[PDB]
Length: 48
Length: 145
Image (cartoon, rainbow over all chains, first blue to last red; front, side, top):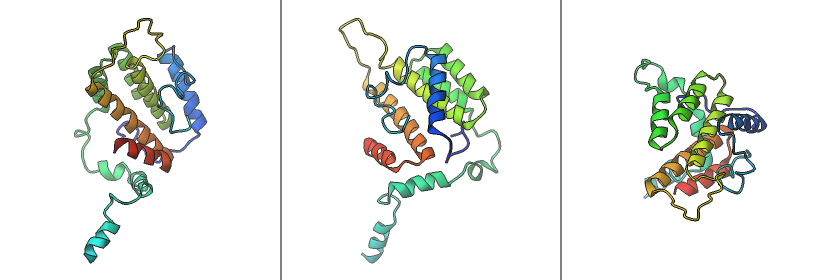
């Protein structure tokens, strides 16, 4: 919260997905989201 | 007993998670930081890197992560980078993409498991709150309880 000083955020969920995918290709270079869905149960609640 | 009934009607614990979510989305940052100086606010970046290195993550990687998080502009990209911290954390521990060529699986201690679970569920709860999703919030409340 002290990093992001705004709750009640707004924006496209699609943009979050694509941005996370891009940052992941940058940082880890190995994993993607299709290796994650129904295999870690992290993003099984949101729509990302 | 009558006042007890009215208290069981409003005590902020038996109320709906819809109401609690709306509260947490209602209150703001400025109303809670203003007046105080810029000194009592501990540098969140230092605490972030400290907790991550406490979780046995690569110092170079997490430092680069936190520096990009500081430098970037935009609430969206910042929370996306946060989720990136989450996934890289949950991949450094609980190595998924590693083919695990050996047959011996040595899982980590229960403390590390609790740390992992808490950070994950907290991040996801904050995100659901930012997006306002009551069934996910209820499910996460269920996980915690």
